[PDB]
Image (cartoon, coloured by chain):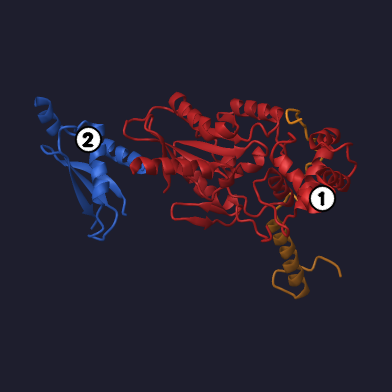
Chain colours: A orange, B blue, C red
Amino acid sequence: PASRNIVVPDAVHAKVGSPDTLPAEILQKRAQRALLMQLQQNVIWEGTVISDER
Amino acid sequence: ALELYDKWNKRVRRAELTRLWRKMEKSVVARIGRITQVNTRPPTFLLQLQTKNDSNTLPKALQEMMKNTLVEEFDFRGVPIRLIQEVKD
Amino acid sequence: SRKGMSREAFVDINEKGAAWYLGHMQLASRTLAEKVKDADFVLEIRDARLPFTTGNPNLQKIIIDRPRLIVFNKAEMSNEDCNRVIQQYYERTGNFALFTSAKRSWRDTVEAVQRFVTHILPAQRFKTTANVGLVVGMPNVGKSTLINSLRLAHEYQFHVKLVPVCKDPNIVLYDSPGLTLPGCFAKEAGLKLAACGIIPTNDITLPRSLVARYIYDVLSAAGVGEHMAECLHLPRAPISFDDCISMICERSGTSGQTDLGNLDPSRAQKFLIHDAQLGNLGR
């Protein structure tokens, strides 16, 4: 039993760029960057071009 | 006896002393940067301390260990060695 | 157990005492590079079950010139084919690799370090000096235990963190307490470490239910259900994680709690009842 070897296929392993693989700090930082940019668009800030819609 | 006198009058290189001190520091207060052999007949080594606090000298255990290292490396076996703790100014 | 944050993922033992290093290894990358530069060789201690996850990415990314010896503990637990391929990879590289079981990592690792220093490490310009090796590894893997053993030996003999190994050829080891700690980690990495047993499981942060579900998922993906059933001694190969838990509880006893039976797969995985691995690589 123990002597028997097991080969894990690469399919089960999560993708390198997946949010699960990425640490939570990076995801939170990107979300907060998006929120700050949204706030800057909502309230007219200097150097902010309104290139979006809605 | 003649060999002991020759060791007493022996000279050491400043570069060798500095490399030995660097290796000792990596192998095992205020550090020192320059070590030189000032006197010749009794081998005396001047070690400079990187601090202006005149009372922040080296521990006696540390200086004895340094003397033992010098004796072991440069073959000052039967020759006494002296150290001088100097502070920058 | 109940407490959420795992201490072993942040804590280590320096000279003054316990410390809680914070942040990711990329922050320490510079200090680690300086330590390796001022050292003479590198001794990396990693876990064979998840080698590339235990290792410090910054070390391999920044320093490759200095000679390095990697010690993969729990080799018997780890898969043989992966061990051999990574050993060949390291042999092609300028570093060295050594796979060790319990007693091997206990003493044969020191013996191999002495052999490495004698054979490949150049000769110093002096004799009283010492060859310095920077030790890099997670304390829970066994680096902390080795450092503590050397510390006790040196203290008994007498009766920055440098621990001597042997008088000849005057080998000493520098300690790196918190340069390769997990700290914050991804969900998949945390699950892998918990399955390997290097990070204790908690009822809040990462439950045993999730850990065992991940173990079952990876085993099913590998397609080893029948062998897992045979190892666990349960009658027939399971079809689901819940079915496996129920079978384990039935085997254990009539009054088999779900959590009690779910705790057994993790212990078996840690105890090598199944031989597997969790980690990728490139060629």
- Which chain does tag 1 point to? C
Q: Is residue C115 left or right of residue B16?
A: right
Task: Give the amino acid type for the residue marked by disc 2 in the picture.
Answer: Val
Q: Could you say where residue C273 lies in the image, as x and y percent from the top left?
A: 73, 36
The residue at the point 71 percent across, 73 percent down is A45
Instruction: Name above or below for residue B19 compared with residue A32.
Output: above
Task: Give the amino acid type for the residue marked by disc 1 in the picture.
Answer: Gly
Q: Could you say where residue C182 lies in the image, as x and y percent from the top left?
A: 62, 50
The residue that mark 1 highlights is C256
Q: Quadrant of residue C165?
A: top left
Which sits in the foreground, C229 or B59? C229
Mark 1–mark 2 distance (CA, rounded to whole Å): 72 Å
Q: Is residue C38 left or right of residue C60?
A: left
Q: Residue furthest top?
A: C119
Q: Quadrant of the N terminus of chain C?
A: bottom right
Q: Quadrant of residue C101?
A: top right
The residue at the point 72 percent across, 36 percent down is C277
The residue at the point 68 percent across, 34 percent down is C77
Instruction: Name above or below for residue B83 compared with residue C11.
Output: above
Residue C53 visible in the picture = yes
Please name which of the two marks, 1 or 2, marks the residue nearer to the observer.
1
Q: Quadrant of the C terminus of chain C?
A: top right
Number of residues whose C-alpha sits closer than 10 Å to that of mark 1, classed few (under 14), some (14–19) or many (20 or more)? some
Q: Secondary structure at mark 1?
A: loop
The residue at the point 66 percent across, 31 percent down is C76
The residue that mark 2 highlights is B71
